[PDB]
Image 1 (cartoon, rainbow, N blue to C red):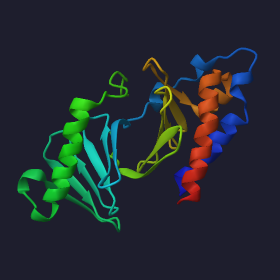
Image 2 (cartoon, rainbow, N blue to C red):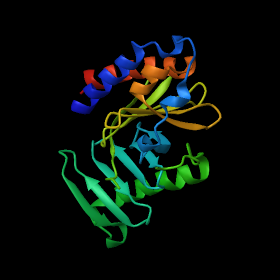
Image 3 (cartoon, one colour):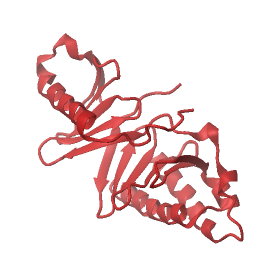
Length: 220
């Protein structure tokens, strides 16, 4: 994929600049407001053992990547749907049209939504949000330390288990959004982090992110 290789040059470049090793870190100068992601995953559910991965995007919409490789999205109007077949074909339905062939998949997805509503906290419920198309989870994996979520607008998001820190990388804006342990949000242009450096926390997570993209390319 083009975007994934684009993101690999961006991440390496920023890492080979050793931004945590500057004389004085001027991280704050690296911030670009024009680079704030339009979409990120706020909540997610790993029912992969029987059904697949359900997630919530920041706009309150939800989606599932089923085990049969199919995909379904529910918009924030709570009725409008998008179904994407295994072989990539998209289509638009309402829930209330009652398609018999999708009721199971509707119900499944509805469970997911209901569940993240009562049982999970919204990651980045604060972030100031910065017109674009609504993406689906292209693919995902988890390791021992994080879960990686690869969206179809090019974006890759990473959520570390240890301490709740998260990354939203966009290869189009060539920008990274870091979410620290206090749920504070900041967006950076990767090349300005090269120039003005950054703290040891963000640098070490960007060093990790690059390995995860090496994992995505290897499995794509």
